[PDB]
Length: 250
Length: 250
Image 1 (tube, helix red, strand yellow):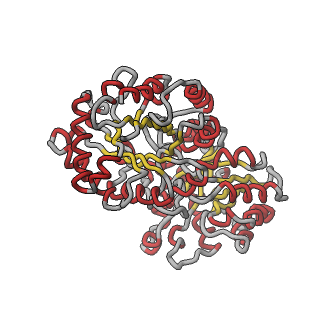
Image 2 (cartoon, rainbow over the protein chains, first blue to last red):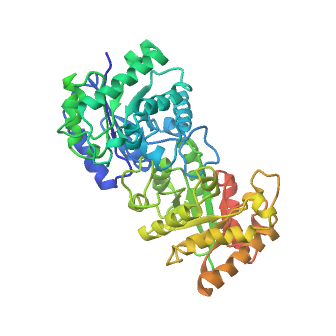
Image 3 (cartoon, rainbow over the protein chains, first blue to last red):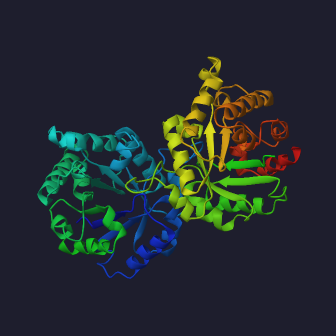
């Protein structure tokens, strides 16, 4: 059975004082065991040392990005081997904001995933379609294309978690229903089964990366092919603890 | 008189063990006073806390990049206000590797410089032309266009240092002479005098960001319009100390 997975993407947010308050609140939380839910917290690069040194040892830390290949003359970038050196176990790759605002292509994302895995990182790999793409009836064409670019470069999926982001509902005034989330997760898992292997489809966590909050987390998490969440803004808030506790619905 | 300035850009390099060795070596160095030379060291984001906590207090730390505007939903990016919060005083912006590989436009760089200054950072702003551009006779056309994009957005130059990168000599098999460096620095300073102000031209450090090592630092540093260096690979090596010591040539 797939272990429920809850990741918290802090995005480009944080100060030393706020990080201290967030971590203290997480440290005082009483949540399901590590056998029931896998919890990953992702601060900006410059707060990885502070968070890794002060966060409860049963929660894990992720970087929000890394470079596509070995380090060297790439001013401003952080290599996967640096993260491994600092004992940062996870990385988020292919987030919708990086695909859209920083123009990361599906192929670029796939090369990053492959390189990160080869260095020993575990990866939250993000996919998702825009409002224009959904309206065009292209949701699964887009999500499959993004996933295929990764699948073409990755032979071993053990340390991958896929995050589906309904970008079409992100600040579009559209809201995503639990039924809509389940439809995409189900079709994506079917795609993995048909295009990678039955074993990979059965064992790979596919987590929901749309709007998740204390109010809707149990309803989303109870969906058959939803294995957890990649949380945005709520991950900065005490409400993240309630989202972790949604693992009990499984 | 303009204070000599030596920045060390570590680029995408470093491990905890190597950082400890580099910092120990700098900490044991005996170099000209803080009144004679201003020294800035720039590690990858994830080593900014380690370096800030262990480096001698009379040397300063820089980030290698920051985001173009206020933080928020920009997964993977580090905002200028984060760096200020962590007491990181400097940032490198517009480095040739980010212009070329990550496609940062001159306008994007200009906006970053303005935002960083607005938040209280000091900025090393990088400009420079390619081999194709130099061979076409466009060196000063290009450097002026890049500088204009920054100047059009900057209201106060006190906390700006300009770095000229002879990109045309970077892995092209061409070598830049000290005379060639001095020509560009002189023409760039004259451009500042005519198009910003005589005071800004007289007071703004323009540092050389081509190949600098122990062997050539004195000849370069002695040029009338060269105010120091943005060092690449030598910045990881004990030789960085000899480059700092070139300040004595002024």
